[PDB]
Image (cartoon, rainbow over all chains, first blue to last red; front, side):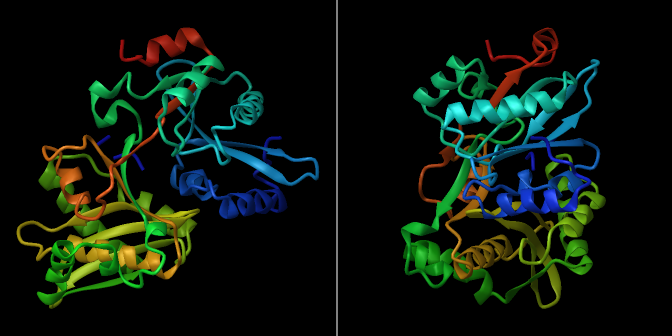
Length: 5
Length: 337
């Protein structure tokens, strides 16, 4: 959830 | 048609299209489904008159707290998405394949935001998520919509990373090397372990969440050493920082990184310089340092990436949602209103 990827 | 994942010849024909397309993205390769092993893959494509693939969309379906799945084609589809009539045709194929199981099909292609393309998509019945949800910050969309991308085609004669930069930046890049930082790379379990040590340390230090090592092992298993490379910066045998870059389509993308606590001797700059060097050595068009939150000196992701990218960040069109169950869509998705 936090940079995507 | 829908791709039969059990027919290796079909799968190879779909991969060849993906790997050779100027619009190819690693998150649309079928190996991404191996990384995202907790999602279910559904892939579709269209063919021209001669039966060649001309467009393809790799979807992954995820659970939700409702009875419908979330269908997501990360950085897809693989085609020119501004050809909206062709996009509609590929999306109709995707919707047939989903067979009423998903409430939405979302895709977030790396194409620039414009008013005309936003309005076209909306005219064609899609719901778009971009400047209307920007106040919610970088995670308003799944992938960052603002990204720092270096266009290497503006430097056709560059031989080394330093050839791309003004003297003040050449100084910043040379510093770690002058101070004894050395960078090795490869895609074995050894480099993965060095990356994972620095990744979990950085995540603890920043108080952010982090993925388990098995995510990266599945990525290593899916992608060969010409596609995935882990760069490891050390000084006199002390591990300092690392990064993982993926070469796919027109870009090498700096995707993951970690660094140890305290003084890292500017090792993160030495990792960038070597990834850039890989892009130059392979005549790759773009080097993507990926997302930021805002084009602002208040944003530490932008402060670091602006060392390497002096152009404005690319701002993409954001999330394009084909709404399939509007009752569930309204429950699960907010429009920034």
